[PDB]
Image (cartoon, rainbow, N blue to C red):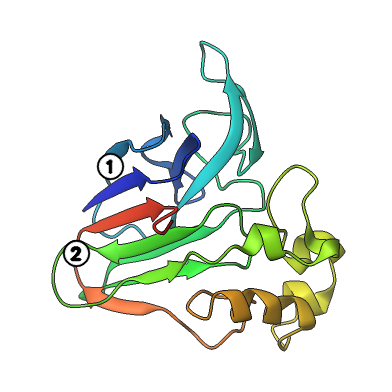
Amino acid sequence: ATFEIVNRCSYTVWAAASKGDAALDAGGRQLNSGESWTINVEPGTNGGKIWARTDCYFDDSGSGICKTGDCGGLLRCKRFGRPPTTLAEFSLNQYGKDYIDISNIKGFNVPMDFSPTTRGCRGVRCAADIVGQCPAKLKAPGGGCNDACTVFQTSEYCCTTGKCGPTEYSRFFKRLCPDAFSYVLDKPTTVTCPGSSNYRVTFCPTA
């Protein structure tokens, strides 16, 4: 499956793609404002994620650091990134179908649209200004808006015991972005697409 990754932001981002124990495609690449990077993700990829990273420095070997979304200091990500990270999430060819969603469970750094390029389903979007409206105690001094699990490390925010409810913090993400996961047990906003769909992830989809 092809995922076109498009940076519409006015600033450079470093796209990342991983299923947590391995890179997807090259795993990561710089996208200046306007650039598009098309990756190929193996069919059957379960638990894949694509995100943006901001304010990165890499040396000639591709080791460095990013202020959001750093995945162990690598250009080419093999693992998930350091919150805060808006997440494009997907499982492909799961009993005949694809599943996609955007999640704010690991916080928010960059607005995102996640849409199929082929027929038979709809896209999802979290494009509100969450960083500028971020509650004071969630602001990440490094840039972005942390989720409350990252900030407070409690059973209620992290949903450790499997029994959490919505919170003042989750309700902020859900209010700004109704169509993205705000906490682990949020009512799902997952979209069912035909198996083997193709996709576009757009950073900063709106003005």
- What residue is at 54 percent from the left and 88 percent from the top? 187
Q: Residues within 10 Å of mark 2 (few under 14, many from 20)?
A: many
Residue 71: horizontal and vertical position, in percent? 59, 39
Residue 95: horizontal and vertical position, in percent? 25, 76
Secondary element under disc 1, as helix, strand or loop, is strand
Q: Nearer the viewer, residue 113 or 192?
A: 113
Give the amino acid type for the residue marked by disc 1 in the picture: Ile
Marks 1/2: CA–CA distance: 14 Å
Mark closer to the chain start, 1 or 2: 1
- What residue is at 73 percent from the left and 86 percent from the top? 164
Going by the image, does 171 lie left or right of 178? Answer: right
Is residue 107 visible in this depiction of the protein?
no
Q: Is residue 102 above or below residue 48?
A: below
Q: Nearer the viewer, residue 69 or 22?
A: 69
Residue 36: horizontal and vertical position, in percent? 29, 39
- What residue is at 46 percent from the left and 31 percent from the top? 76
Q: Residue furthest top?
A: 60
Q: Which quadrant holds residue 133?
A: bottom right
| Residue beneath disc 2 | 197
Q: Is residue 54 above or below residue 94?
A: above
Q: Which quadrant holds residue 64?
A: top right
Q: Nearer the viewer, residue 24 or 75?
A: 75
Going by the image, does 25 lie left or right of 172? Answer: left
- What residue is at 59 percent from the left and 75 percent from the top? 176
| Residue beneath disc 1 | 39
Residue 72: horizontal and vertical position, in percent? 63, 34
Q: Residue furthest left?
A: 119
Going by the image, does 18 lie left or right of 153? Answer: left
Give the amino acid type for the residue marked by disc 2 in the picture: Ser
Image mark for residue 173: none
Is residue 181 visible in this depiction of the protein?
yes
